[PDB]
Amino acid sequence: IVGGKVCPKGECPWQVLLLVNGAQLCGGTLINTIWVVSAAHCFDKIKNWRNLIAVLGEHDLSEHDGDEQSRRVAQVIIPSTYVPGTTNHDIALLRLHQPVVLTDHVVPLCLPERTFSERTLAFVRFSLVSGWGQLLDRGATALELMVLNVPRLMTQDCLQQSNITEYMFCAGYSDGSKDSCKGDSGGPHATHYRGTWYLTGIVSWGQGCATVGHFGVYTRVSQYIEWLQKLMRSEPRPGVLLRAPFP
Amino acid sequence: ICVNENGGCEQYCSDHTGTKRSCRCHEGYSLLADGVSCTPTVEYPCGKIPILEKRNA
Ligand SMILES: Cc1nn(-c2cccc(CNC(=O)Nc3ccccc3)c2)c(O)c1-c1cc2cnccc2[nH]1
Ligand SMILES: [Ca+2]
Ligand SMILES: [Cl-]
Ligand SMILES: [Cl-]
Image: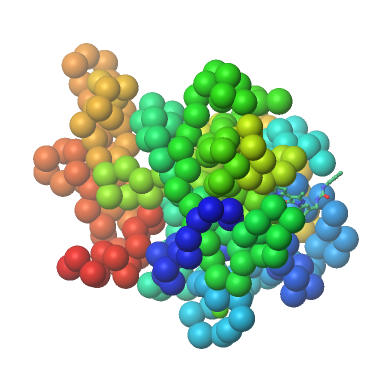
């Protein structure tokens, strides 16, 4: 996150940190005790699928304070329509090997109904994007969980103000001040409505961050609700990586 | 209608045949008798921030 602030500890309780061999991979979003939503691209290069760790209740990466909860990733589910090294259908559903324990510091974000998400949430101007990504373009990553308020653009308006599909949306600023960025991917775009927070977006990717004349690109989660819901009701299959048809 | 003002619903909303409308609530919530409002039924419902909820309790 560029141009953001520190998320006070426990105020981003749905935020997930993904690790590979102890190394920062990506972000994620907790939607249930065993389910995490992330970005498909995060997994393009995964060699040993068995070394994937999800961390909940994380905040300051430099310390252990005891609120942290680590789980192995038992399943990574990706839409069939996703092509590695691209942007379209940049979504992933992760199954935890064991449920996390809900606490003050570990809470899931509401996965909304499609209709609600479409007719209502999609019109809430401002939403919150978070992560432990780069603080700066070509910069170091954050030790402390960062958050950023970003406005959402209609796709028409996005293009005017500038490959955007119906599976994406634009959010942010073009002045180059404020953006989500490398290391943030798979993180939540979280939208408030009537005292509750919802999963509207996933930090995808693009060229740079905080690139003048550009807007941040996010996976349009509303497009995936039914797909996600069906998967969550399904029995685990052997092998970590699973390609599931979309729609 | 659900398309307008969210049908007055705090959360989820379904249109029915006629001038009929049904509000709903996410798991870990219950619908109040006003037929629009949702209240938590659990300690840690989704999309709520405990330290902030407690800060106002
Ligand atoms: C760059 C970049 N690299 N990863 C990355 C993070 C984790 C695993 C993999 C491995 N996947 C792979 O290499 N696929 C692939 C496949 C074929 C060709 C090239 C790449 C990449 C990112 O998240 C970004 C990223 C940029 C960006 C800008 N603004 C907002 C967010 C942003 N995120
Ligand atoms: Ca820590
Ligand atoms: Cl099944
Ligand atoms: Cl495997």
